[PDB]
Amino acid sequence: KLSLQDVAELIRARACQRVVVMVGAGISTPSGIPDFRSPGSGLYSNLQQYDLPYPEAIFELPFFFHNPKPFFTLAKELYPGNYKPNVTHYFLRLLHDKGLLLRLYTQNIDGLERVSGIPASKLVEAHGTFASATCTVCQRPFPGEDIRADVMADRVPRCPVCTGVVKPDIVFFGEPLPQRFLLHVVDFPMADLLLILGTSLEVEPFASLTEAVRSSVPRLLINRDLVGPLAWHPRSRDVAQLGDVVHGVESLVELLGWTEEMRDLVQRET
Amino acid sequence: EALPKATGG
Ligand SMILES: *CCC[n+]1cc(CCCCCCCCCCCC)n([C@H]2O[C@H](COP(=O)(O)OP(=O)(O)OC[C@H]3O[C@@H](n4cnc5c(N)ncnc54)[C@H](O)[C@@H]3O)[C@@H](O)[C@H]2O)n1
Ligand SMILES: [Zn+2]
Image (cartoon, rainbow over all chains, first blue to last red; front, side, top):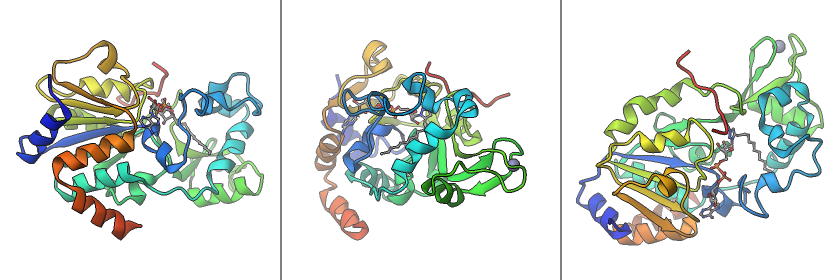
């Protein structure tokens, strides 16, 4: 089997020059944002006070059309927080600074990839963004700040033209993904390394991307535990660094010899 | 038609 040191040596020799990355909410728990499925602390274990038929309903499009108030109540709790990127985000920026990042596919809606300096064309926000919004009736677009302003004032955002409910451009369950998700069609067959960080690989079609790389390509998981195909459909060149994501990234950085570059980047940015 | 919908599976 391959080790983490083997992956670091492949990168250092530039045998791997074209890295695709898949991330989820586990990369932002070190920044103070809860994930969805962790025992005790995950969002799905902490929605009892909301007016929901079941927890998952708060992120489902048909329920949003039925009653959007629980979703906006929850959003009011994320807007004020001044979350910052952590070492995981800056490591992905360092990959770009070294010319190794092919594309970063994220499920997160916290915006921290952009804050850490990943350029828009290298980034696929596969489940959308709070940065923009769309009227659910007339489909007119609006900046995300308008929605933020209404929500923090305890109002459901309504369209100034038709009075329909205006929704942030996040992909709810049951909603189409953005067109740029289709970059995966070319990105994954030519990637020469896949990095998977902080995700349960439970949501589709995002999770199916893990099988789109070639069988000859290593898949490196940095996560608290084995998940998805890495758990039940493993491949011979899979590597798992099971533990905290910041500790795993710092270990990889040390094996790569990138400690000075990481420190310089974090200093500049913080 | 080519754009997929998000599911729990
Ligand atoms: C088809 C579309 C489905 N979809 C849409 C969305 C987004 C809905 C809107 C969200 C609004 C959030 C508001 C928050 C307010 C907060 C106020 C304070 N989603 C979302 O659900 C999916 C979640 O999947 P995930 O893989 O990203 O997250 P999980 O929690 O399921 O798994 C996390 C994973 O990471 C590990 N882990 C956590 N912390 C770790 C550390 N420190 N180190 C290592 N590993 C860590 C956990 O053990 C677990 O394995 C996404 O698709 C998201 O977009 N879905
Ligand atoms: Zn409208």
